[PDB]
Image: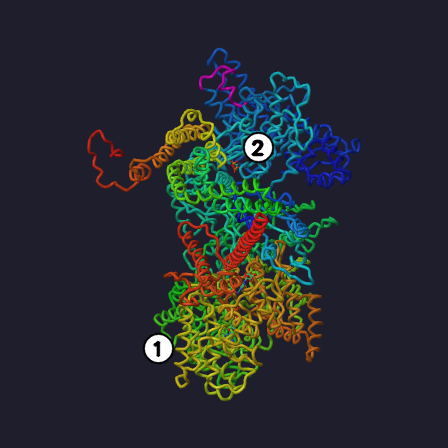
C-alpha cells in the first residue's frame, strides 16, 4: 500500500521508516532516472537540488526534521509560466522546471513532530511496524508456509477481481487478432475451435470461481481464525523483545532478528519433519517458536534476568492459550498490587509469622 | 621555520613548555635577555629570573619568584656559548651541580648541629639563613634519617642502651629552638624557612616517638622501611646519584631541580598512605589516580611528593582552559626532560577531548611500562613513544598522575587508584598552630576543626561561604600574624602568657564576620561560645578612625553611630572594610542593591585621607559597560601593536606615577557585576601573585598602595576561584535602615540649594515634614504596607524613596515659583504647611503603588486615609489618585485641568495628535516633576495604552528639550548609544575633564529609549546597555574607550517606556539600575476618558457631514460601550490574540472617516450602517466559535438600538452588510449578489492568467476578500491572518492585491538568512513604498520569522510607521535624495531633512500594507487587524467538491434515495442526486479524518494536522483515478465491439 502511495501522488511524499528498507526501495526504483542521495544537514544540498532541478533528476533528502524552508516554493508546486517557459523563484535565483522531476523527503525516526506548514504540503507515507502490521505479516507468512493451498486460494480470490478479467480480455483480443488474420476460413476451423474451446474452459473456470467465492472466503476465514493465536503470540514476542531494552542497554534487538527466529522455526524445524496433521503442526510450531525465541534471546542475556524473560513468555503463552482463566487480578496483585497501603489492622496473628510477612 | 622551532625544542627539551610564538620570541630576542625572564617561570619549577652580569654576558646565578637567589659555584658565560640552547642547558646543569654542592655543605653543617645538645640559636639562624628553604629542609631530613639509621644499626642486640631516645631528645631541643625563634621578628624568607623546618621536624618527632619506639630495633624492620628514609653519599661524581631517596622497596634519585620557596604540605596519615601508594605505583611503572572529593588534598599531595623528590611538577587544570596544540608538546616535554604532570580533575574534560588525552596518556604509560621489562631491564634501545605523530624518547623519571572525583577504560589497567576522601584536619591544624608559635597547638586544633565543621553545617548555605581546609589554613596563618603583632605591641612598652584562644577567636571573627549575612552572625557567635566556653572577642577601638569617620559623615550628610545607635551596623561594616583593607588587597564589597556599599568605601577613603594625610583617589570602572577587549586592550593580528585597555591604562598610569601617583591611596572600584569572562586576567593580580599578564608580554605589578574593589550586588555568576582569593565584606540590607535614609534626605534638603531664599523655603518645608519621617511615622508605615502590595516591577525601597524625594524637591520648587509669581505677599507659614502636607500625601500616593493597577492604588489610598491625620478629599466616590494639590493648598480634581481641544478634520486619528485626558494630565505633571531633577523614568503599561505618544507629546511640549526616539531591539548594545552621542553630541576638553554635551546650546537632549527592557539578557544575567545607562545615571559619566578618559555627561537625560516584564520577550531590569528610575504604570484609559477623547474625534469627524453633527455624542457613547463589552469578555485566557486596546478604537474611527471622506450627504442610516460594518470587521471576525460571532452581532445591534432608539432597524435585519468600491466610484454598501458575480469573474480571470490552479469561490472566501480589500483600503492598514496552513490565506491576499493594483512582496527565507538580509529587505520595501507612490502588499508568514529581531523590527514598522534604525550614512543620504525627487514629482518643497522624513513616513503609512499569517506576542496581535481565517466549513467543503467534480460523468438516473446521511445541512436538493451524494460522501470523508485525528489525540497522540490542501489533493486524485479507470473501461468496451463486428464478418466469410 505504501508503494502504491509512492507511485501515484501529487504532493511530494515524505518517507518515514525506522529501517532503511524504504530508502533502498526508492533507490532501486529510480536508478534508471539517476536518483541522487542528499541530506538537509549537508552544505552541498542547495547545489545538489539546483543541479537536479536543472536536469529533472529525482532527489531524496534525509534528515527531514531539520527541514529547509527554501524548499517551500518547490513543495507548493508554484509555477511562473511565462513566455512558454515554466519558471520558479528559489530565493534570489530563478530556475526552470525540467519535467519528470520528483523529490522524496526521508527520515529514520518514527517520532518526529513536523510543523503544520510542512504537514500540508507533503503526503505522509509510514513504514513503522506496529502490532497489526507484524500480526498480519506473520499471518501471511504462516498461511504461505503451512497451508500453501489456502494461500493459493487467497491469491486466486485476490486476482479474480481484476487480474483474471484482464487475462480473459487479453485472450479474447488474441482470438480477435487471430480471426482477422485468418479471415474466418473454414480451413482454419481446427485452430479457431481449439482457441475458442480454451477460452470457454477459462470462462467456465472463472464462473466456477465466482460461484464458489463464498465457500472459499469462509474456508479462508476459518483457517485464519485457526492461525490467529500464533500470529498474536508472535507480535507479543517481538514487542516484548523490543521493549527488553529498558532493563539493560545490552538488550537491543531488531525486526530482522525476530524474522530470523520466525523463519528458522517455520522451515528449518526438526520437529516438523514427520508431522503432517495441521493442528499438530500448529501446536509444534507454536511450542518451538516459544522455545527457540527464549533460547536465542537468553544466549546473549544476563543470567540474573533469564527468569524475567521466561516469565514474560509464560504470560504471553497464557494469553495465547485457550480454556484458561484470564488471571488479570492475581497477576496485577503479584506485580504491583503488593504495594497498596494496608498498614491498618496488622495483627501479629500466629507467632511464627513476622511483621512484614503479616 | 616550524622545523627549526622543533629542532630548537629538541636541543633544549624544556622549550616544549613554552609556546610556538613564545619560542619565536625567545629565538628572535636571544641577544637581549630582558625579555627572557618573563617566560623563565614556565620551564623551571621556581626559577623566575637569572642573575646576569652588568653587561648580561655571564649568568652568575638564578633567582626565584620570592626573591631567593642561588649563586652558581662556577658561573657560565653567554659570550662563550652564544646559541640559546647550549647555554641554557649549561645553566640547567650548573644549577643542579650547585644545588648538590650546597646540599653537601649544608649536610656537613647539620651533622655537627644535630650531634649535639642545647644548640645555640645564633649559629642555627646563621645556618638557615645561609641556605635555601628547600636546602635546609633536605639537610634536616638527611641528618635525621642518617642519625636514626645509625641508631638502629647500633640496636642489633635489642633495646639495651638505645640512642633513639637521644635522637628524640635532639629533635625536641631543635623544636624548642625553632619555636623560640619563630616567636620573634624574622624576615619573611627566614619566616618561611622556619615554618618548613618546624613542620618537617614535627613530622620527624611524631615518627620517631611512636612509629620507631614501639620496641623496634632492626634497621631492616618494615616499620622503619615504610617511612621515608634519606641516604646521602657525596662521594658520587654524578650529581643525580649523590642523594638517594627510598620508600618501602622503591628507590629514586633526587632530581635536584630548583623550586624556590614552595609551600611545604603538612605530613598526615592520609598524606603518608598517599606517598606509599604513589611510590609503589611508580616502582611498578604505573600511573597514580588519587581520586576523591575536591578539596581533600589530591593535586597538592602529588605536587608535594614531586617537590620531595626534587622533580618539576606541572598542573593542567581542566576548567575549560584546555587545548591540544599545547598539551601534545608539553607531554613531549614531560617525556623528554623528566618532569611530572598532574591533572586537577579529569572528569571535567569533554568526551572527545578526554578520549584523545586518554589515548596519548595510554601511549606514554605503555612506553613507561615497557621501560621496565624484566627481560629488557638493560634498556639498550631507547624507550620511545608516539606523540605528535613522531618518535619521542621517554625518560624513566617522568611520571603522570590523573586526579579524579571514573577512570576511562583505557587506563584502568595502567593507573593505581587511591581514595583520599577525608584528610586528617586535626593534625593539619595542630602542625600549623605549632608552626605559628602557639604552645598549645593540639587543643586549639581540637577546638577549631569541629568549629569549622559546625560553621559548614549550622550556617545557612551560601555560594560565597567557604569553610574548606584552605579556609581553615588561612585563618590559622592570620592568627599567627595577629599573635606576632600583639607580641610586638606588648614588647614595645617571655611574653608567653597570652590568651591564645582569644587570639584565634579574634582571627577567625576578623576573617569570617565580614562575610556573614546578618542572620548568621548570632549563629556564628553561639557556635564560638559552644566550642570556646567563655572566651570573648574584643574589637579594636580605632578611636582616631572613629573620629575621622564621624567628621566625614557629618560633612557628607550621613548618620553616624556606635554599636546599638542608628547606623552602628553601617559603621561596623566600614571598620570591617578597613581591617580587610589592612589584611589584604582585592576586597569584595557585596550586598543587596540599595545597601550602603559605594558610599561606605567613599567615606572610608576620605577618612583615611584626612587621618593619615595620604591623598586618596578612587577610579570607578564598570566592567559590563564595555567589552572585555577594550577593558584590557587589544593586540593587532597584523601589526602586532598593542593598545592598552581601561584597566591596563589605569594600572600603567599608577605604576609610572608621572604626576606622583604613588604616595597616594589608589583604589580601582569595579562597580557592576562579576562573571568569569572579564575576571580571568584578574586572578593573577588578585592573589599573592599581584602581577598582570598582558598577552603581548608586558608585565605589570600591583604596587602595595593599590587595592582592587568590586562593588557587586549578588555575587552569583562568579567562580569559586575569584571569591576564594578575596577578603570579602557583606553589606546586608538590614545594615541600611530607612531612618538614616530619611535623615540624609532631610539634611540634604536643609543644606543643598535645589538650584538663600530657596534655602529658607527648603528649611521651612523640611521643618514641616520632619514629623512624618519618623521611625513609625506615615512614610515608614506606608512603605511597609506598599511592600506587601503588588507592583508591575520588583519594588525596591531605594527606588521608591528616591522618587518620593524627587517629588518633594519639585514641591519645594513649586513653592519657590509661586513666591516668584507674587513678589508681594509671599507664601505664608500656614499655607505652606497645608500645601506641603497635602503634597506629601499625594507624593506617597504617586510614588508608592504608582507602578500598580488602579485597584491597588485605591487600596493604598484607603490605607493612607486610615493611617494619616492630614485632611483628605472629602468626596467618597472618587479615588484620591484622581485629585491633586493646588498651589493654594487644597485638593482639586484633575478633571478641572483637562482642556477641551477641537482638532481639524484631516487630523482625525493622526499618528501624532494627542487629546488631553485625566491620565494624560496626570502623567504630564509627573513627567515634568521628574524631569526637573533629570531623573530617568520608565513608563510601563500594556501594549497600546498610549505610553509612547503621551511621552512624545509631553517631551515636545517643553521648548528647551530635544527629543530623540531610540528603539531598543533585542540585540541592542552600547555602540548604538555611542553612535547617538556622536551624531547629536560633541566632546569638549576645555574644563577639568572631557565633557560630552549636545551641539545645540541650552538644549537638554533627552534620549527617549522605548522598550527599555527588550534588550536580551546575556549568559551571566546582565544587560550591557542597561548597565551602561546606570553608569551614566549614578556616576554622571562614562569612560570614552578611544583614549580611556572619563568624559562627564552634561545636559543629557534618559527616558524609557516598556511593556510589563511578564510579556514574552521582556526581561526584568536589574535592581541596581531600577533604583534610579521611577516607574509609572500607564493602565488602559478609563471609560470616561475614552468617551471624552473619542467624542472629540467624532465631533471633528462629523463636520464633514453637517446633518449628523448632533449625532456624534451617541455614536461615541455606543462605540465606547461596545468596546467595554468586548473587553470584559474575550479575555486573553480564552485565546492568545484576544487583546483589546484603544488602538482598536483609533483604527475604528479612521475606518469610519475613510468611508465617509468621499461620500456626501449621508443620512443617519448610512452612519449607523458604517459603524456596524466597522464593528463587525474589527471585532466579530477575530473570534473562533460561532457563538462568539453571534453574541457580537446581537450585542452590536442591541447597543445600536439602545443609543439610537428613534432610528429604525433598516440597518439591522441586513445580515451581510457588505461594503465595496469596485462597482461604483466610492465605498458604497453594495448588494451581495452582484458583487459576488463580479468577484467570481475577477478571480476567474485571476486564476486564468496569474495562477495555475483553479480557485473556487464560497461565502467564506467572499467575506474574507471583503475584509482584505477593506484593510488595504485604509491607511496604516495591516492584517493579522490566523488560520490553519493551506487554507489559502496567502493566495486570497495575493488575489486581492492583484485586483486592487498593489504589488506583492515576499521575503524569500532560507537557512542562511540573517538579520542584515532582513533589514536590507525592509530598506528595499520602504524605499519602494515611501520614495515612490507605489503601493506594496507585504506577505508575512510564520515560517519567514526565525529570530525575535525580525518580529521587533516589524513591530516598530507597524506602530511607528517607519524604523529609524534602517537608514544611516550613505543609505540615509540616498533616502534624502530619492525622497526629495519624490517630493518634487508630487509637487512639494523639500525644506530640510526632518520635514522630508516626515513626508516619507506619511507616504509609507499611506502607501504600505503588511499582511501577517500565523497558525493558531501581544504586541503583534495589537497594531494589526486580527482576522480569523478558520478552517473550511462543511458548506465550504461541499461547494469546493461540487465545483471540482462537475467535469466528471457522475450522473446516474437510476439512483435510489436512501434515508439519513445527515452531513451537509444545506444539501442542495431534498432528495440528493448521484453527484450530490458523492460530494456529501467526500465531505463526510474529510469530517471522519478530522474525527479520527481527534480520537487519536485523545488516546495517546502522534497526530498530523489535516488541512484543506489534503482535501484538494484527494479531489485531484479522485478526478485522475475516475477519468483513468473510465477511459480504460471505455477503451476495453470499444475493443470488444470492434472485435464483435470483425467476428461477424468472419462468420459471413464462414458462410461464404
Ligand atoms: N550614614 C550613612 N551611611 C551610608 N549611607 C547612608 C547614610 N545615611 C544615608 N545613607 C544613604 O544610603 C544610601 C547608600 O547607597 P549606596 O550608594 O551605598 O548604594 P550602592 O551600594 O551603590 O547600591 P547598588 O547595590 O544598587 O549598586 C544612599 O541613599 C545614602 O544617601
Ligand atoms: N490621549 C491620547 N491621544 C491620542 N491618541 C491616544 C491617546 N491615548 C491613546 N491613544 C491611541 O492609543 C494608541 C496608543 O498608541 P501607541 O501604540 O504608541 O501606545 P503605547 O501604549 O505606548 O504602545 P506600545 O507599548 O505598543 O508602544 C494609538 O492608537 C493612539 O492614537
Ligand atoms: N597534606 C596537606 N597538608 C596541608 N594542607 C593541605 C594538605 N593537602 C591539602 N592541603 C590544602 O588543601 C588546599 C587545597 O585543596 P585542593 O587542592 O582543593 O584539594 P584536592 O586536590 O583534593 O581537590 C590548600 O589549602 C592546601 O594547602
Ligand atoms: N478557495 C479556494 N479554491 C481553490 N483552491 C484553493 C482555495 N484556497 C486555497 N486553495 C489552494 O490552496 C493552495 C495553498 O494555499 P495557501 O495560500 O498556501 O494557504 P495558506 O496561505 O493558508 O498557506 C493553493 O495552491 C490554492 O490552489
Closer to the camera, B288 or B197? B288
Quarter of image, res B1369: bottom right
Mark 1 → mark 2, Cα distance in angstroms = 81 Å
Is residue B259 visible to the viewer in this orientation of the structure? yes
Q: Residues within 10 Å of mark 2 (few under 14, many from 20)?
A: many
Q: Which residue is mark 2?
A: B303
SS at circle 1: loop
On residue B1382, the disc is: none
Q: From this view, report whether residue B158 is shown above or below residue B1035.
A: above
Label 1 or label 2, whichever lies nearer to me, is 1
Residue B856 picture quarter: bottom left
Point out the image quarter for the N terminus of chain B.
Answer: top right
Of B390 and B865, which appears nearest the observer? B390
Q: As rendered, which of A232 and B1522 lies closer to the eye?
A: B1522
Task: Give the side of residue A330 with respect to residue B882, left or right.
Answer: left
Q: How many marks?
A: 2
Q: Is residue B989 magenta?
A: no
Task: Give the answer, above or below, for where B1490 lies relative to B1391.
Answer: above
Q: Which residues are magenta?
A: B214-228
Residue beneath label 1, please?
B876
Q: Is residue A275 above or below residue B1332?
A: above
Which callout, 1 or 2, points at the residue further toward the start of the chain? 2
Quadrant housing residue A136: top left
Amino acid at each position: 500500500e505504501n508503494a502504491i502511495m509512492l507511485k501515484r501522488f501529487n504532493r511530494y511524499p515524505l518517507i518515514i521508516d525506522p529501517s532503511g528498507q524504504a530508502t533502498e526501495f526508492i533507490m532501486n526504483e529510480y536508478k534508471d532516472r539517476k536518483i541522487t542521495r542528499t541530506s538537509f544537514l549537508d552544505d552541498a544540498f542547495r547545489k545538489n537540488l539546483e543541479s537536479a532541478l536543472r536536469f529533472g533528476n529525482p532527489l531524496l533528502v534525509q534528515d527531514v526534521e531539520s527541514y529547509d524552508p527554501v524548499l517551500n516554493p518547490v513543495l507548493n508546486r508554484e509555477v511562473r509560466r511565462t513566455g512558454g517557459r515554466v519558471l520558479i523563484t528559489l530565493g534570489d535565483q530563478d530556475i526552470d522546471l525540467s519535467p519528470s522531476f520528483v523529490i522524496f523527503l526521508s527520515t529514520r525516526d518514527p517520532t518526529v513532530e513536523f510543523p503544520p506548514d510542512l504537514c500540508s504540503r507533503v503526503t505522509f507515507v509510514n513504514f513503522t511496524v506496529t502490532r497489526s502490521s507484524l500480526q498480519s505479516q506473520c499471518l501471511n507468512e504462516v498461511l504461505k508456509a503451512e497451508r500453501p493451498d489456502v494461500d493459493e486460494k487467497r491469491s486466486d480470490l485476490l486476482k479474480l477481481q481484476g487480474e483474471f478479467q484482464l487475462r480473459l480480455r487479453q485472450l479474447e483480443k488474441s482470438l480477435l487478432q487471430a480471426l482477422n488474420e485468418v479471415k474466418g476460413r473454414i480451413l482454419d476451423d481446427d485452430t479457431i475451435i481449439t482457441t475458442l474451446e480454451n477460452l470457454k474452459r477459462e470462462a467456465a473456470e472463472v464462473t466456477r470461481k465466482v460461484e464458489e467465492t463464498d465457500i472459499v472466503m469462509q474456508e479462508v476465514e476459518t483457517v485464519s481464525q485457526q492461525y490467529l493465536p500464533l500470529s498474536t503470540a508472535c507480535s507479543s514476542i517481538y514487542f516484548t523483545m523490543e521493549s527488553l531494552k529498558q532493563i539493560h542497554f545490552l538488550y537491543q534487538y531488531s525486526l530482522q532478528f525476530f524474522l530470523d527466529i520466525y523463519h528458522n522455526v517455520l522451515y528449518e524445524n526438526p520437529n516438523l519433519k514427520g508431522v503432517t496433521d495441521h493442528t499438530q503442526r500448529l501446536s509444534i510450531i507454536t511450542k518451538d517458536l516459544f522455545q527457540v525465541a527464549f533460547n536465542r534471546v537468553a544466549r546473549g542475556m544476563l543470567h540474573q534476568d533469564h527468569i524475567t524473560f521466561a516469565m514474560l513468555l509464560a504470560r504471553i503463552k497464557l494469553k495465547g492459550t485457550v480454556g484458561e482463566p484470564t488471571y488479570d487480578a492475581e497477576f496485577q496483585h503479584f506485580l504491583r498490587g503488593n504495594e497498596i497501603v494496608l498498614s491498618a489492622g496488622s495483627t501479629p496473628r500466629i507467632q511464627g509469622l513476622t511483621v512484614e510477612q503479616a | 621555520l616550524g622545523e627549526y622551532l622543533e629542532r630548537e625544542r629538541s636541543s633544549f627539551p624544556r622549550f616544549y613548555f613554552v609556546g610556538d610564538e613564545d619560542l619565536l620570541e625567545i629565538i628572535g630576542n636571544s641577544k637581549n635577555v630582558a625579555k627572557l625572564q618573563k617566560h623563565f617561570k614556565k620551564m623551571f619549577a621556581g626559577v623566575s629570573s637569572i642573575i646576569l652580569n652588568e653587561d648580561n654576558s655571564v649568568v652568575l646565578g638564578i633567582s626565584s619568584r620570592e626573591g631567593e637567589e642561588v649563586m652558581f659555584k662556577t658561573p657560565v658565560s653567554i659570550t662563550e656559548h652564544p646559541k640559546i640552547n647550549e647555554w641554557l642547558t649549561l645553566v640547567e646543569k650548573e644549577m643542579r651541580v650547585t644545588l648538590a654542592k650546597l646540599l653537601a655543605e649544608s649536610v656537613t653543617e647539620v651533622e655537627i648541629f644535630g650531634k649535639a645538645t642545647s644548640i645555640d640559636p645564633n649559629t642555627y639562624i646563621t645556618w638557615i639563613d645561609k641556605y635555601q628553604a628547600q636546602l635546609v629542609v633536605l639537610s634536616a631530613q638527611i641528618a635525621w634519617s642518617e642519625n636514626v639509621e645509625t641508631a638502629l644499626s647500633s640496636m642489633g642486640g635489642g633495646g639495651d642502651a638505645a640512642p633513639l631516645h637521644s635522637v628524640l631528645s635532639n629533635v625536641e631541643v631543635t623544636l624548642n629552638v625553632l619555636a623560640d625563634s619563630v616567636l620573634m621578628e624574622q624576615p619573611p624568607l627566614r619566616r618561611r624557612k622556619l615554618e618548613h623546618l618546624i613542620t618537617e621536624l614535627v613530622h620527624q618527632r611524631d615518627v620517631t616517638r611512636s612509629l620507631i619506639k614501639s620496641k623496634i630495633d632492626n634497621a631492616k624492620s618494615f616499620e622503619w622501611l615504610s617511612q621515608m628514609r634519606f641516604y646521602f653519599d657525596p662521594k658520587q661524581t654524578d650529581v643525580l646519584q649523590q642523594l638517594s631517596i627510598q620508600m618501602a622497596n622503591a628507590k629514586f634519585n633526587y632530581g635536584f631541580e630548583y623550586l624556590g620557596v614552595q609551600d611545604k604540605l603538612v605530613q598526615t596519615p592520609l598524606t603518608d598512605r598517599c606517598y606509599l601508594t604513589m611510590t609503589q605505583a611508580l616502582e611498578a611503572r604505573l600511573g597514580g589516580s588519587p581520586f576523591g572529593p575536591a578539596g581533600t588534598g589530591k593535586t597538592e599531595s602529588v605536587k608535594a611528593l614531586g617537590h620531595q623528590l626534587g622533580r618539576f611538577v606541572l598542573v593542567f587544570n581542566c576548567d575549560e582552559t584546555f587545548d591540544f596544540q599545547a598539551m601534545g608538546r608539553i607531554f613531549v616535554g614531560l617525556c623528554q626532560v623528566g618532569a611530572w604532570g598532574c591533572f586537577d580533575e579529569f572528569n571535567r574534560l569533554e568526551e572527545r577531548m578526554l578520549s584523545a588525552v586518554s589515548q596519548q596518556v595510554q601511549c606514554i604509560q605503555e612506553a613507561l611500562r615497557e621501560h621496565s621489562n624484566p627481560n629488557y631491564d638493560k634498556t639498550s634501545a631507547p624507550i620511545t613513544c608516539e606523540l605528535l605523530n613522531k618518535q619521542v624518547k621517554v625518560s624513566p623519571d617522568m611520571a603522570i598522575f590523573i586526579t579524579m572525583n571514573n577512570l576511562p577504560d583505557n587506563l584502568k589497567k595502567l593507573f593505581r587508584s587511591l581514595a583520599m576522601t577525608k584528610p586528617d584536619r586535626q593534625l593539619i591544624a595542630q602542625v600549623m598552630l605549632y608552626s605559628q608559635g602557639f604552645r598549645t597547638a593540639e587543643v586549639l586544633a581540637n577546638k577549631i576543626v569541629p568549629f569549622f565543621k559546625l560553621c559548614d553545617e549550622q550556617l545557612s548555605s551560601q555560594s560565597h561561604y567557604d569553610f574548606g581546609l584552605r579556609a581553615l589554613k588561612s585563618v590559622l596563618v592570620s592568627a599567627g600574624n595577629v599573635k606576632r603583632e600583639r607580641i610586638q605591641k606588648i614588647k614595645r612598652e617571655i611574653a608567653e602568657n597570652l590568651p591564645e584562644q582569644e587570639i584565634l577567636i579574634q582571627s577567625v571573627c576578623e576573617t569570617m564576620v565580614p562575610k556573614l549575612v546578618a542572620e548568621d552572625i548570632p549563629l556564628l557567635f553561639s557556635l564560638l561560645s559552644d566550642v570556646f566556653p567563655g572566651v570573648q572577642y574584643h574589637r579594636g577601638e580605632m578611636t582616631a578612625l572613629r573620629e575621622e569617620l564621624k567628621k566625614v559623615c557629618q560633612e557628607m550628610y550621613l548618620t553616624y553611630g556606635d554599636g546599638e545607635e542608628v547606623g552602628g551596623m553601617w559603621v561596623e561594616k566600614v571598620l570591617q572594610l578597613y581591617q580587610i583593607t589592612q589584611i589584604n588587597h582585592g576586597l569584595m564589597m557585596v550586598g543587596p542593591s540599595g545597601s550602603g556599599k559605594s558610599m561606605a568605601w567613599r567615606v572610608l577613603l576620605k577618612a583615611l585621607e584626612r587621618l593619615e594625610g595620604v591623598e586618596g583617589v578612587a577610579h570607578i570602572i564598570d566592567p559590563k559597560a564595555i567589552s572585555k577587549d577594550h577593558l584590557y586592550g587589544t593586540l593587532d593580528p597584523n601589526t602586532r601593536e598593542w593598545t592598552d585597555g581601561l584597566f591596563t591604562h589605569v594600572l600603567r598610569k599608577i605604576i609610572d606615577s608621572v604626576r606622583g601617583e604613588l604616595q597616594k591611596r589608589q583604589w580601582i572600584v569595579f562597580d557592576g557585576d562579576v562573571d568569569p569572562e572579564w575576571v580571568e586576567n584578574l586572578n593573577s593580580v588578585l592573589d599573592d601573585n599581584k602581577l598582570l599578564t598582558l598577552p603581548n608580554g608586558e608585565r605589570l605589578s600591583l604596587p602595595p598602595n593599590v587595592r582592587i574593589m568590586f562593588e557587586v550586588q549578588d555575587l552569583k555568576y562568579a567562580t569559586l576561584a575569584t571569591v576564594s582569593r578575596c577578603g570579602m565584606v557583606w553589606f546586608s540590607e538590614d545594615v541600611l535602615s530607612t531612618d538614616m535614609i530619611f535623615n540624609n534626605f532631610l539634611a540634604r534638603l536643609r543644606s543643598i540649594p535645589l538650584d538663600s531664599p530657596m534655602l529658607q523655603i527648603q528649611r521651612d518645608a523640611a521643618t514641616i515634614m520632619q514629623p512624618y519621617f519618623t521611625s513609625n511615622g506615615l512614610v515608614t508605615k506606608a512603605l511597609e504596607h506598599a511592600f506587601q502590595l503588588e507592583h508591575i516591577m520588583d519594588l525596591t525601597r531605594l527606588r521608591c524613596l528616591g522618587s518620593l524625594f524627587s517629588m518633594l524637591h519639585q514641591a519645594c520648587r513649586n513653592v519657590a515659583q509661586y513666591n516668584a509669581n507674587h513678589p508681594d505677599f509671599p507664601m505664608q507659614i500656614e499655607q505652606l504647611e497645608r500645601y506641603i502636607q497635602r503634597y506629601l500625601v499625594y507624593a506617597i500616593l504617586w510614588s508608592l503603588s504608582g507602578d500598580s493597577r488602579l485597584k491597588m492604588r485605591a487600596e493604598l489610598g484607603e490605607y493612607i486615609r486610615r493611617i494619616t491625620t492630614v485632611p483628605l478629599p472629602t468626596a467618597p466616590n472618587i479615588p484620591i489618585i484622581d485629585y491633586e494639590v493646588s498651589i493654594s493648598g487644597e485638593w482639586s480634581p484633575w478633571q478641572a485641568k483637562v482642556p477641551q481641544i477641537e482638532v481639524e478634520t484631516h487630523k482625525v486619528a493622526a499618528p501624532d495628535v494627542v487629546v488631553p485626558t485625566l491620565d494624560t494630565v496626570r502623567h504630564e505633571a509627573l513627567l515634568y516633576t521628574w524631569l526637573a531633577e533629570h531623573k530617568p523614568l520608565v513608563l510601563c503599561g500594556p501594549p497600546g495604552s498610549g505610553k509612547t505618544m503621551t511621552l512624545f507629546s509631553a517631551l515636545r511640549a517643553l521648548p528647551d528639550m530635544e527629543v530623540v526616539g531610540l528603539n531598543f531591539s533585542s540585540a541592542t548594545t552600547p555602540e548604538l548609544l555611542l553612535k547617538t552621542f556622536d551624531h547629536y553630541c560633541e566632546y569638549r576638553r576645555t574644563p577639568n575633564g572631557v565633557v560630552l554635551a549636545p551641539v545645540q546650546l541650552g538644549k537638554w537632549l533627552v534620549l527617549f529609549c522605548d522598550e527599555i527592557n527588550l534588550p536580551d539578557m546575556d549568559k551571566y544575567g546582565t544587560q550591557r546597555v542597561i548597565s551602561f545607562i546606570r553608569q551614566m545615571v549614578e556616576h554622571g559619566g562614562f569612560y570614552r574607550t578611544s583614549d580611556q578618559t572619563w568624559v562627564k555627561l552634561e545636559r543629557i537625560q534618559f527616558v524609557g517606556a516598556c511593556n510589563p516584564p511578564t510579556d514574552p520577550g521582556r526581561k526584568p531590569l536589574s535592581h541596581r539600575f531600577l533604583r534610579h528610575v521611577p516607574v509609572v504604570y500607564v493602565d488602559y484609559p478609563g471609560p470616561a476618558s475614552l468617551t471624552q477623547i473619542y467624542g472629540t474625534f467624532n465631533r471633528a469627524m462629523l463636520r464633514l457631514i453637517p446633518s449628523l453633527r448632533t449625532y456624534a455624542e451617541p455614536l461615541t457613547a455606543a462605540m465606547v460601550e461596545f468596546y467595554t463589552m468586548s473587553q470584559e469578555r474575550f479575555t486573553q485566557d480564552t485565546q492568545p490574540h484576544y487583546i483589546y486596546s484603544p488602538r482598536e478604537m483609533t483604527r475604528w474611527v479612521r475606518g469610519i472617516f475613510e468611508a465617509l471622506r468621499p461620500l456626501e450627504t449621508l443620512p443617519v442610516e448610512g452612519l449607523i450602517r458604517i459603524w456596524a460594518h466597522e464593528a463587525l470587521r474589527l471585532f466579530q471576525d477575530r473570534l473562533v466559535e460561532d457563538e462568539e460571532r453571534r453574541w457580537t452581532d446581537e450585542n452590536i445591534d442591541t447597543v445600536a438600538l439602545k443609543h439610537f432608539p428613534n432610528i429604525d432597524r433598516e440597518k439591522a435585519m441586513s445580515r451581510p452588510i457588505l461594503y465595496s468600491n469596485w462597482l461604483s466610484k466610492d465605498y458604497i454598501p453594495v448588494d451581495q449578489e452582484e458583487l459576488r458575480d463580479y468577484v467570481k469573474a475577477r478571480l476567474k480571470v485571476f486564476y486564468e492568467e496569474e495562477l495555475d490552479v483553479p480557485l473556487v469561490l464560497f461565502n467564506e472566501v467572499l467575506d474574507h476578500v471583503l475584509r482584505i480589500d477593506r484593510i488595504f483600503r485604509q491607511p496604516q492598514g495591516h492584517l493579522l491572518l490566523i488560520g490553519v496552513s493551506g487554507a489559502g490565506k496567502t493566495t486570497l491576499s495575493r488575489f486581492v492585491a492583484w485586483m486592487n493594483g498593489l504589488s506583492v512582496y515576499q521575503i524569500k527565507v532560507h537557512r542562511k538568512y540573517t538579520g542584515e538580509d532582513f533589514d536590507e529587505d525592509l530598506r528595499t520595501v520602504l524605499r519602494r513604498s515611501g520614495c515612490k507612490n507605489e503601493k506594496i502588499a507585504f506577505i508575512m508568514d510564520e515560517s519567514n520569522v526565525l529570530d525575535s529581531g525580525f518580529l521587533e523590527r516589524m513591530n516598530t514598522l507597524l506602530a511607528n510607521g517607519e524604523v529609524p534604525g534602517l537608514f544611516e550614512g550613505d543609505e540615509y543620504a540616498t533616502l534624502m535624495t530619492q525622497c526629495k525627487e519624490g517630493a518634487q514629482k508630487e509637487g512639494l518643497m523639500l525644506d530640510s531633512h526632518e520635514e522630508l522624513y516626515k513626508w516619507f513616513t506619511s507616504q509609507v503609512i499611506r502607501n504600505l500594507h503588511v499582511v501577517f499569517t500565523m497558525n493558531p506576542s501581544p504586541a503583534l496581535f495589537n497594531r494589526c487587524v486580527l482576522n480569523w481565517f478558520g478552517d473550511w466549513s462543511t458548506e465550504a467543503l461541499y461547494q469546493v467538491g461540487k465545483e471540482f467534480t462537475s467535469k466528471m460523468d457522475l450522473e446516474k438516473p437510476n439512483y435510489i434515495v436512501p434515508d439519513y446521511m445527515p452531513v451537509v445541512y444545506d444539501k442542495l436538493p431534498q432528495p440528493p442526486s448521484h453527484r450530490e451524494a458523492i460530494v456529501n460522501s467526500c465531505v463526510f470523508v474529510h469530517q471522519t479524518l478530522h474525527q479520527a485525528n481527534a480520537r487519536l489525540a485523545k488516546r495517546g497522540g502522534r497526530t498530523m494536522a489535516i488541512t484543506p490542501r489534503h482535501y484538494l489533493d484527494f479531489i485531484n486524485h479522485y478526478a485522475n483515478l475516475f477519468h483513468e479507470k473510465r477511459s480504460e473501461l471505455e477503451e476495453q468496451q470499444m475493443h470488444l465491439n470492434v472485435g464483435l463486428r470483425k467476428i461477424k464478418e468472419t462468420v459471413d466469410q464462414v458462410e461464404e
